[PDB]
Amino acid sequence: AKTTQEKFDALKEAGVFSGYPGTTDAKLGQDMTRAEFAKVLVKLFGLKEIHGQYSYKDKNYDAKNWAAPFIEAVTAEGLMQGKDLTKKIFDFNGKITVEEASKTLVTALKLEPVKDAQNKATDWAKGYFEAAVNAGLFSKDANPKANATRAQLVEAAFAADEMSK
Ligand SMILES: CO[C@@H]1O[C@@H]2CO[C@](C)(C(=O)O)O[C@H]2[C@H](O)[C@@H]1NC(C)=O
Ligand SMILES: CO[C@@H]1O[C@@H]2CO[C@](C)(C(=O)O)O[C@H]2[C@H](O)[C@@H]1NC(C)=O
Image (tube, rainbow, N blue to C red; front, side, top):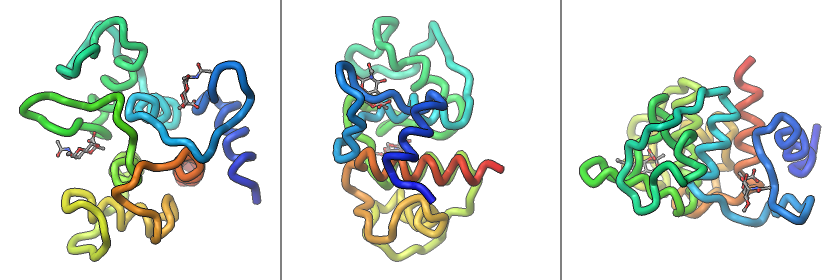
């Protein structure tokens, strides 16, 4: 049993995570954009990329956006939907939150969301967060509304990959 840095080393090896330019530093106290997390999900679950397609109307969401193949893939898969359907906004530059990540992983893992869960999560996310908590993907005193740290995401990702046989 294996430190957060060691889990990151393993996930980086398997191409799931990448680090930052000019440094081998994992920066586990830093946040992560929704674009970066979409990639992580794609690699975590071996989803196929989707090129030449753009389903969202965010500014600079187009063929010059390195993240679009990943954002399209997690969207076809049902793991992510964006933040509103009417305006078709994904918010690729915003940071992934623990309750958002929770949604994605609970769904990818086909776990049962909890009806009428009591916790601090946003309404739409309460069953997702509670299920993610009970799966050991996030700690029960993580803040569901806070941006997830890279440490928390390494831990959640590593645990999730375990749950896939
Ligand atoms: C700003 O450079 C980027 O940093 C990103 C950090 O978060 C993740 C999910 C990661 O793999 O660590 O994605 C990284 C990008 O791949 C990119 N990294 C590099 C080395 O250019
Ligand atoms: C603001 O509405 C929420 O946005 C969340 C963004 O993160 C994810 C994981 C997403 O699907 O991309 O979950 C979204 C929630 O379902 C919710 N989005 C909607 C359209 O209701």
